[PDB]
Image (cartoon, coloured by chain):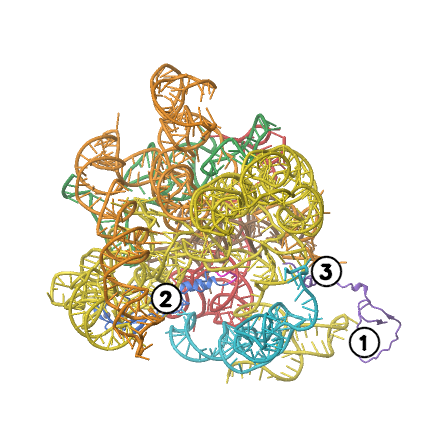
Chain colours: A blue, B purple, C brown, D red, E green, F orange, G cyan, H yellow
Amino acid sequence: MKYPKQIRTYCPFCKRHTIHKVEKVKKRPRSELSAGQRRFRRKLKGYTGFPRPNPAGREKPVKKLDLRFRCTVCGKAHTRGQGFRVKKFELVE
Amino acid sequence: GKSLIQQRRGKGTTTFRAPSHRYRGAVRYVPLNLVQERTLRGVVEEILHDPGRTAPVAR
RNA sequence: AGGGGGAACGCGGGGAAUUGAAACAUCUUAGUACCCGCAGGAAAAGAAAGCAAAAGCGAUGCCGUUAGUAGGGGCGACCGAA
RNA sequence: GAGUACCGUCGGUCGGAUAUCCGGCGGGAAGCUGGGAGGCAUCGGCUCCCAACCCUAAAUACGUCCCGAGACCGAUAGCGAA
RNA sequence: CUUGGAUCACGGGGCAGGGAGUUCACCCGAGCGGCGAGGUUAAGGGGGUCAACCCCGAAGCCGCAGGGAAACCGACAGGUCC
RNA sequence: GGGUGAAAGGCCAAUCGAGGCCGGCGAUAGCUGGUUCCCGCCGAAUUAUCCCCCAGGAUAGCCCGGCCGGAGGUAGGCAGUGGGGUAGAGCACUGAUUGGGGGUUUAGGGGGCGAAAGCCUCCGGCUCCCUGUCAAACUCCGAACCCACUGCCGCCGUAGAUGGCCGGAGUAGGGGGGCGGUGUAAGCCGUCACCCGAGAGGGGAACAACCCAGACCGGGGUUAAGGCCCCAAAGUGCCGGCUAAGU
RNA sequence: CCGGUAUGUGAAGCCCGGGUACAACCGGGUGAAGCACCGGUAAACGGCGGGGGUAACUAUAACCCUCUUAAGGUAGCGAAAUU
RNA sequence: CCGUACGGCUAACCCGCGGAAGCGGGGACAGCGGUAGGUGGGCAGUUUGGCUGGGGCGGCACACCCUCGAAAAGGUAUCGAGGGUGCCCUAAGGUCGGCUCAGGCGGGUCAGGAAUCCGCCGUAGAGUGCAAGGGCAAAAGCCGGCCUGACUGGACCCGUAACAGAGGCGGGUCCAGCCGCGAAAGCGUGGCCUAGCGAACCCCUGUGCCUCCCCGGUGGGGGCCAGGGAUGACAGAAAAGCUACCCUGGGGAUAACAGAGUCGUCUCGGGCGAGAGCCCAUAUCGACCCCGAGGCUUGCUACCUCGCUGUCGGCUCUUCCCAUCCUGGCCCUGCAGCAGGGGCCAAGGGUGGGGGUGUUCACCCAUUAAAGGGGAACGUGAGCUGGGCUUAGACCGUCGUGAGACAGGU
Ligand SMILES: [Zn+2]
């Protein structure tokens, strides 16, 4: 499925219609400074059976996109609607 | 499970223990302490069968 | 000079599983049952390198509240002070 | 008042959570112009204290015994045992 | 028990004695009673004819103001109709 | 969870695929058994969704007790305003299905006068007329019947309707009878909501649910279902006809 | 199972850089065993199949190539305590 | 300046001789302590789902959409019938304008002509992004132009789930904001309508604000709103097997087992008449198609019994039925006689002995008047036997990594 690189849409910060660049969100790993990770690490210590579920082999064949739209005037980004599923995703002019 | 024979041998029971009380003594050389350079001499008195040596001993 | 004995109460160490979570592994049962050592008519604690917060208090122990609160926790079942 | 305060890592325990206490291992001070605490760590102020030695009654817990009492049972009951 | 018991479905030789919704903690309601924008004491103290009785003790808890994760903000004691 | 075993899971004080004694321990179980006086008022359910759920639970539905409120409600019927596509019927669409005629004559194999796809026929398709048949997943048609609403009749209701709040439950194996799908059938799965379950009495010879009929107590009468030769209360009843096989 | 090996991967620790008035934290490098790689071993566990075709008339595939796969049941025994 | 390995040494440490002092050998290795990775059924704790005409193998009726079932409002189940979805698309999305399809016939190309050219008829017999049903013609279809309303902040309502309760998920009617198309009115919150999807805790990203224990700063944490990362057993555990050494609690809610029901199958028959029989349907035989009885074979079902008895066969003992094998009496014949076929009445009496096999049955032998067949809880274990079958021991073959298993053999 083809998709444009730029689109004219409403900007909630400027409160008018402007041209927006389309970007995909890049995932990143768990931060060690976070409280959930602190708790996981302090419950993984010592003599203990594994304390949490461990789902291996859990991968939907098709995922929803996570798109962001960045304005050229204001420099800020937002999201536009919910995400839709499709295997192929090309950005074109 | 249950134990093996070689595991039961390690605990040291009569079923696995050597009857050394039946044997002639241990066979060892005289110590160097007494043989600094003295070169003692001896004479054989008797030849004897030992049940724990696979070889005959001499006194 | 010591050893041994003494119902319950006392001090210091070692330490489960049934069970509940409608299965179960973190958890719970539980610092529990049981085990080892050491004292007395009471033992232990005890005279701030503390608590607090623009005000101040003045060793320790016990009762009533604070409170099923702060907080912990497959943030589930539950646990739980000052 | 030194292998101490403190730093890191492992194990246990705690409501103690990046902020509970105990222990092992590796490092390791100042010491009166000195030192510590104030719930993540560091900086500056303000407040409060002086560890790493010792002793201490009363207010409390119990009842193998003793005294007194009872909307307790009344010999298949009441402690197993009148 | 069961859709279904006179059943070839289970329990049933006779008599007398024993024998099964109890206590605590929190919560939701009600039938009565006291005080009432306020209500109520706990531990404990004093007195006495000394476990009954009388007088103190409002610490705390609930209610009179709510909304909000929080910082924070902060309302008719009566205008009209059926 | 150790011993011993020329190995059989054999033996370890009548106890062994992990001894015996006491303790944890009044372990736990959605599974089985039991649960103590009388009368009186009311009175069910086994069906929807969810649960490692199917011998168990929760949320609703169906019962009971109390209160609020204050003027209507609707298990039946009549007339109307609208809705529907079943039974039946039929071929107007989709698909099937006999045969005889009138045509184009052909995409196409056998071909025949084919001096070679050929002009002519020829078995074949398609096109109108007859003729004979069909449909759970067809319809040019189309009931009885059911549903919603308005008005009226009827019935209930100020001795308190529709409704609302508070509280206490039980029910999560249903069965007979009628209808529908399935199945050789018996049976399986649903549906209606009359009965049994939870219902005495009078009859069918006896019969859970077929017929009459719903029950405080003591009495007197008339009928119902059915019956009237004896068993057995009541007719060896009346008129016309049939049967000769104890049918 | 055993042995060997250049490279690769590989935890803590150590080093370098960035960051933090210090730390927590981020990226890279090095990094033993083991894994990977290369070889030996069946009186180790185990395996010993497939076809597409047959020379002289009735049956023979008894001989020879093949492509599947590490290889393709040898001597003996056989309706067997195995049919 | 930091490391790593190689060589050597002795004084720590270790081993041996010793009554001890000391001697000899090894040696900064080992051993001991702390920490980090691997291997590890040697040892433990657990899990190994459900529906199901018993259970298992099989399948998914375990999440969704359409038609029939389904009974002309609504609602209605079965391992009921017929099928589909777990996507795709920057256009197949929005709007404006213009146009009209399939097929057939008549002309012209031509192997059918697959398609291009011409005219006419033609209510859709076409097409729609994809199943089925429904909708649609100056269109919702075809050809083109301009666009991104496939948007932000928010309300109310309907369905999943009637009546009668719901987290999450779909959908509908609108208010504001900023925009697109269009002359304008008007339409536009994805796809003509109905499928294409998912809790809590935790993490990632965006954006502007609140907050961290006496106060103020810095780094780093916690909070509110929005979008993504998954659980198909699809209202969401992190998860492999054997028991024939097996135990506990239950179940006739559920099999083997006899009984009840049923009779497809089984045993025994009938009707009609194609024919075969030298000719002649019917001495005898009798197709195809139709109608039955019995309950003695096997199946189907699951009403009865889960410690009633759970067994097959044989021996022994008694009794009944007739659909009659012999014995008594009759009829027809393709009955000369001797014998044979077929049928009627009759159940009084008879129906035996042996070989192999656990056998019933079937097969064979010699006799015989003939050596019939069934029922009685597949008659009969408080009558016998114990050969088979169906516990615990053991061997073979095959299957399995293995523990093991085999309506296979011993
Ligand atoms: Zn902008």
Q: Nearer the viewer, mark 2 or mark 3?
A: 2
Quadrant including the N terminus of chain A: bottom left
Q: Residue H367: x, y in percent? A: 71, 44
Residue depicted at 87% across the width and 76% down the height:
B42
Residue with the mark numbered 1: B34
In space, the residues marked 2 and 3 are separated at their CA atoms by 69 Å
Q: Is residue C66 above or below residue H125?
A: above
Residue with the mark numbered 2: A62
Q: Nearer the viewer, mark 2 or mark 1?
A: 2
Please report whichever mark, 1 or 3, sits nearer to the chain's N-terminal start: 3
Q: Dot 1 lies on which element?
A: helix
Q: Dot 3 lies on which element?
A: loop
**Badge 2 vs badge 1, beta-carbon distance below 8 Å:** no
Write the start and end of the magenta stretch as one range. A46-51
Q: Is residue H152 above or below residue F80?
A: below
Residue depicted at 51% across the width and 60% down the height:
A49
The chain under label 2 reads A
The chain under label 3 reads B
In space, the residues marked 2 and 1 are separated at their CA atoms by 92 Å
Q: Tag 2: Cα neighbours inside 10 Å, few (<14), some, or many (≥20)?
A: few
Q: Which mark is residue B13?
A: 3
Q: Residue H274: x, y in percent? A: 44, 50
Q: Is residue H101 above or below residue H47?
A: below
Judge whether residue B46 can be spotted in this image: yes
